[PDB]
Amino acid sequence: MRVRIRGIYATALTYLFLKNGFEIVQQTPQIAERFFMDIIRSPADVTVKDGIDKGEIVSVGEDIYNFMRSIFKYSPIWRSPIKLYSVVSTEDCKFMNFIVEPCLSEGLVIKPPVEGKIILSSPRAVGKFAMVWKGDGRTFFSEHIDERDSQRLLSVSIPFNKKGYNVKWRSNAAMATTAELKEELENLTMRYSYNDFREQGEDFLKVTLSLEDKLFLDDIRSLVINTMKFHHMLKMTYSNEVDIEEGKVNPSPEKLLTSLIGDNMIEAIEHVKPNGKRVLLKGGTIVQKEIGRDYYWLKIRREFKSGGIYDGLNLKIEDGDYDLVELDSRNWYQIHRYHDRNNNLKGLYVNISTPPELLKNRIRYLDLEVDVVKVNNTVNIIDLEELEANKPILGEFLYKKALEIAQNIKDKLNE
Ligand SMILES: [Mg+2]
Ligand SMILES: [Mg+2]
């Protein structure tokens, strides 16, 4: 299969796709040079790029799920049951088990249901190179079409604009022969006029990368060009700063890591659920930290006001209650020590997760559902059934690893 790759993971991903037999196409000149390969100006069967959040990789086109699940063992992967750019029929503003927006009775899926919500637009006939529908008769271009390639495309779609068809050129169109393009618009306009959208959808998946797989990608990228530890994690906040440091004699991520939690304050903990939803949890003051060449550790103090129950502990939250949270880049867990205003220990909550990432004034981790709670000398592994519910997207390796950690923590808490 021919694959097109963009975004902060592109070098590491290019290595791994090559290593697994894919044809790389539409390389940038800088990718071509790094892999000593020719730029192939051919359409891609599948496109891999950053998600809306740079901590995600998305894939659109042919299904590569089984391949992605074997590269990324320690990351949730969601395969869309709904093909992107399919056309669906709606009732009561629902399609199957999903909400749609807007509430079109017939609509083109333009965003998959990552969290149970499908984004629609008015139907269009979609091929690999173009989308067509009825309108004024205008030609639109993907952002990723160079100007040198636009005029050829316009010459093809102008006739169809005259007929009242809007034409959206997709970036793959720039690599297609002119005869392919003409055939494409002939077929698309004909299918549109018959209201025929069968089999037009494209497969979609999203990898929510853990720090474990980001470090694996740092290692892979290291085989091609100079790469610091935490390179990809830092590329969520920094751009050229990371490359500058990687040109130095012994590159270290220490200063850029320190800058993220510069002022010893965490405004929020991003608790990422298996499905990708980022849940903001209360932050606090960094009372102690250690940032080295290849790891970081922090102790955060979180202040609580009256209100509610502490999850797992089943204890009421009182004014002046505080949490001492220990987290470490090498650890798949955070130890929360819950105290009252007079420093009395209320309980211990061990949050199980993928290794914590650093963002500007924020911590991020992929929560693994199972937790371990200790109150007095009661030590309980909780929410095993919620880890089970999330096994299809977590995959078996994260699932097994969260069971090992849980057992380990219980044994330690019981000593
Ligand atoms: Mg948890
Ligand atoms: Mg829970």
Image (cartoon, rainbow, N blue to C red):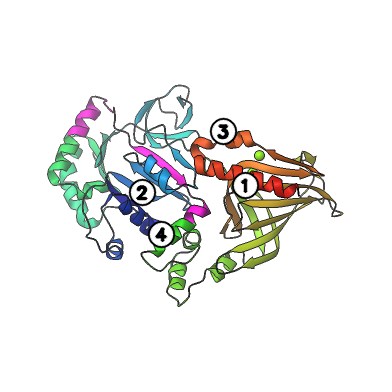
For marks 3 and 2, the one nearer the N-term is 2
Q: Position of residue 39 (x, y in %)?
A: 23, 58
What's the magenta region?
187-214
Q: Quadrant of ligand 2?
A: top right
Name the amino acid type tagged 1.
Ile
Q: Quadrant of residue 191?
A: top left
Q: Secondary structure at mark 1?
A: helix
Report the residue at 84% width, 53% height from top: 341
Q: Quadrant of residue 90?
A: top left
Distance from the alpha carbon under mark 3 to that under mark 2? 28 Å
Q: Residue furthest left?
A: 179
For marks 1 and 3, the one nearer the N-term is 3
Tell me if mark 3 has few (under 14), some (14-19) or many (20+) residues whose alpha carbon lies within 10 angstroms of its own. Answer: few
Report the residue at 27% width, 48% height from top: 171
Q: Judge depth for marks 2 and 4 and give the one in front.
A: 4
- Pointer 3 residue: 389
Question: Which residue is more in the foreground, 369 or 155?
Answer: 369
Query: Where does the N terminus fall, quadrant-wise?
Result: top left
Question: Taking 227 as reference, is 155 left or right?
Answer: left
Q: Would residue 345 be seen by someone viewing this image from the given angle?
A: yes
Q: Secondary structure at mark 2?
A: strand
- Pointer 4 residue: 220
- Pointer 2 residue: 48
Whether residue 209 is in magenta: the answer is: yes
Queried on whether the Cβ of the residue with tag 4 lies below 8 angstroms from ligand 1, the answer reads no
Distance from the alpha carbon under mark 2 to that under mark 4? 17 Å
Name the amino acid type tagged 3.
Ala
